[PDB]
Image: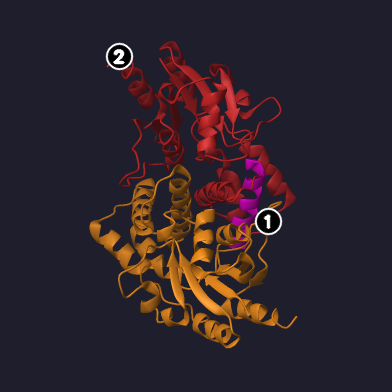
Chain colours: A orange, B red
Amino acid sequence: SGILVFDVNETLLDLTSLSPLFERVFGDAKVLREWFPELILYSQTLTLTGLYRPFGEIAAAVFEMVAANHQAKVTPDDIAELKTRLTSMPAYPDVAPALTRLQDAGFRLVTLTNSAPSPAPSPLEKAGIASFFEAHLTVHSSQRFKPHPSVYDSTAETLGAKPEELCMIACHIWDTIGAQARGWRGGFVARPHNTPLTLAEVPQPDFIGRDMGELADQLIASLTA
Amino acid sequence: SGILVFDVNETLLDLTSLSPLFERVFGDAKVLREWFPELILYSQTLTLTGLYRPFGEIAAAVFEMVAANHQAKVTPDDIAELKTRLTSMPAYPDVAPALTRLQDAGFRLVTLTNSAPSPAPSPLEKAGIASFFEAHLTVHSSQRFKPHPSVYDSTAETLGAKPEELCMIACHIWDTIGAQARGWRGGFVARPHNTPLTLAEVPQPDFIGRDMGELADQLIASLTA
């Protein structure tokens, strides 16, 4: 049927589980929606400038920067808590059922994350959904972050797959744009606080679902059309 | 003496002048600090994937996306207002004095912006500070945004200048990182809600000021130390 390549943080695992840390440190859970795009921004800046550091180190550095920007106090224990929550986000309840149906439909399932290879147990293992996937790939071998082309290309090469066989699944349009620019298909799942970007000559996702169930429905239905 | 290459939006011109629009549309002026990094994120995503649209178009599209993320209504009026405000930000009071001091100390002054060329009068002309600068450069001919190396390289090329003669000045650490990776110096001015990113292996700015006056102190001091 094809190979479905899933983004992990926010797409499969619930980023809003971090909200209490932001509520406490900043007095405002909404700062999550400042910090996260700043993290992605700086990951792309390092990539563009020829620098690489593991994603989690950037996450901590950006948390400290955002703290400083809000004049909010941060301790070594706050950073520890950030690590704890970021590496242990629970799976949305729509995930295990959707992955089950995609497997039943004959799709091969893979993950691809900006996060560095993790000591066991990984975030996916802690969430109890790691075993759905035949491979768990990361940006390690590319030393560059999404949406750099090397990331998708090295993934395709690793899987022995052509672009036409692959579909990148994410709640981040930057990730689907990245994959589609390399000739993959893109499937967008509309997690809270994520919507597509409508901009001329920027590719729109091939599939859109309001949640993982609906996206899976569309992926499965497109097999019979 | 050297050439000082200034970022424009937020660095020289006051981005908080947009706050009332965010207050009206979102009920919360602080959404400025979610939209702006999303805008920079998407500018770098387009650059990484080989796509280009003018910065203002991205700004509008990201405004619409952030609005949708907040379930906030957006009208054509709001979009025209964003355009008007983004092209009419006033100069901070500290700018003209700092530029006068730097010019009188013998520095050559240039601007470099992600923003596309405008018809006259430019935002810098309207703000009354365009005359300090010998050149006004943009990423538009490069069709790539900061911090892509092409931006800084094509700038040095246009000026007929060597990297050792150039210093990038910005309140955005992504911009200084971009320039320093090309062997320019970097000068950071700490505009409200901007602070440096402390990350191993990523160069710190050569010069740091809490305002343009303090940064100019440091630049001027470096001439005879």
Residue that appears at 45% across and 57% down? A36
- Rendering quarter of residue A192: bottom right
Q: Is residue B18 above or below residue A72?
A: above
Q: Is residue A37 above or below residue B109?
A: below
Chain of residue at mark 2: B
Chain of residue at mark 1: A
- Magenta span: chief secondary structure: helix
Label 2, on which residue? Answer: B224
Q: Position of residue A158 (x, y in %)?
A: 48, 67
Three-letter code for the amino acid on which mark 2 is drawn: Thr
Whether B65 is among the magenta residues is yes
**Quarter holding the N terminus of chain A?**
bottom right
Three-letter code for the amino acid on which mark 1 is drawn: Thr
**Quarter holding the C terminus of chain A?**
bottom right
Q: Is residue A92 above or below residue A169?
A: below
Whether B5 is among the magenta residues is no
Label 1, on which residue? Answer: A198
SS type, badge 1: loop
Number of on-image labels: 2
**Is residue B123 at all visible to an observer of this figure?**
yes
Between residues B54 and A142, which one lies in front from this camera angle?
Answer: A142
Q: Among all residues in the image, which is located at the extreme front?
A: A160
Graded by Cα atoms within 10 Å as few (under 14), some (14 to 19) or many (20 or more), the crowding at tag 2 reads few
Q: Position of residue B33 (x, y in %)?
A: 50, 49
Magenta stretch?
Answer: B53-71
Between residues B171 and B13, which one lies in front from this camera angle?
Answer: B171
Between residues B68 and A126, which one lies in front from this camera angle?
Answer: A126
Asked if residue A223 lies left or right of residue B149, the reply is right
